[PDB]
Image (cartoon, rainbow, N blue to C red):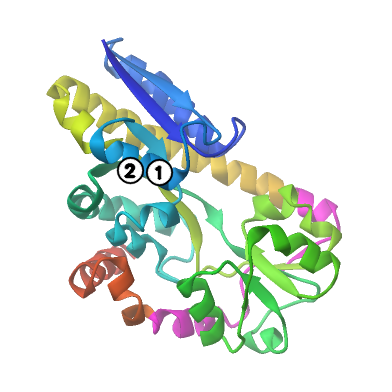
Amino acid sequence: DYTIRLSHGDNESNPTHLTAVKFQELVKEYTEGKAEVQIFPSNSLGTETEVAQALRMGSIEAEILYTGNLVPLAPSAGVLMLPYAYTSTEQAHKAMDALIDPLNERLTKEAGVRALGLMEKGFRVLTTNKPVTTLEDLKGLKIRVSPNDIAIKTFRAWGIEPLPMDWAEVFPALQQRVIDGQENPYTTAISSRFFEVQSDITEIHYMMWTGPLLISERAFQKYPEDIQQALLRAGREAVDYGRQVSAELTEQSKAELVKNDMTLHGAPKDEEKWEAAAAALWPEFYDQIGGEEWATQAIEIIKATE
């Protein structure tokens, strides 16, 4: 009856894909069979941003993508990236799910997309070749960030100029000992084998990997309310499920990094200092994330849930 092409940029063992499959099987269920989802993983249909454009005009019906690749089309989505907005996944879940509706009011006007669910795949934790348990421990460290304003300004707010570098340079830079550490999820430190070149991990909470499960707003509207309400449900559940898949993969990654001789210090002893420094930056991001009216509303909602 109806066919949903769903794009994403990861391989099939990723919680992203697993999330996709759940959405697939769940869609088949609530529409009895009137709707089928086909998954196109691993960037088969293009880049995450290109594909986002495909959704605008209806070419491709769905995708899971990193919030950062959506922002260029839909700035309002950038409120999902405010530094230190959440300190835990559970808290984050609650705050985002409160954002979805009003956020969707802006996603549709800006990019002809609607979020069926907001995914997250863990915090960008700090790795180092020495323990960092307080702000002062950051001093003198060369930490690479990806070339974005939020990462760059946050680390600066914390007393060090981070090194904006390309992903591909990060490992070699570590191995050659020409930088001191970096920040990514626990999963990356495993996949990238960062334990061969790093000794410590501190669980800062300035950033998570977030990404909407988007439906095209055209494809969505074309559908009979029977189809719509089913996709709305399958999506929230596929994400709740994927969120849980990620958590598990994270506990597993952790237990393994430790088996590979890394020390996991949990949060910073003086975390409220990191949070404070990061949170004061917020008004400096309003313009790149949809404007002060939306940013502040977004902030109002997030904090209320907290």
**On the image, numbered disc 1 is attached to which residue?**
50
Is 197 positioned to the left or the right of 278 in the image? Answer: right
Mark 2 nearby-residue class (10 Å; few <14, some 14–19, many ≥20): some
Residue located 33% across and 37% down the image: 54
Task: Check whether the beta carbons of the residues at disc 1 and disc 2 lie within 8 A of each other.
Answer: yes
Front in this rendered view, residue 80 or 3: 3
User: Residue 98 sits in which quadrant?
Assistant: bottom left
Residue 136 % position (x, y): 67, 89
Residue 80 % position (x, y): 37, 60
Residue located 16% across and 20% down the image: 226
**Given the image, on which type of amino acid does mark 1 rest?**
Glu
* Distance (Cα) linking label 1 and label 2: 5 Å
With respect to residue 138, does 26 lie above or below?
above
**On the image, numbered disc 2 is attached to which residue?**
53
Is 113 positioned to the left or the right of 194 in the image? Answer: left
With respect to residue 6, does 209 lie above or below?
below
Front in this rendered view, residue 182 or 53: 53
Q: What residue span does the magenta drawing correspond to?
A: 256-281
Is 23 positioned to the left or the right of 153 in the image? Answer: left
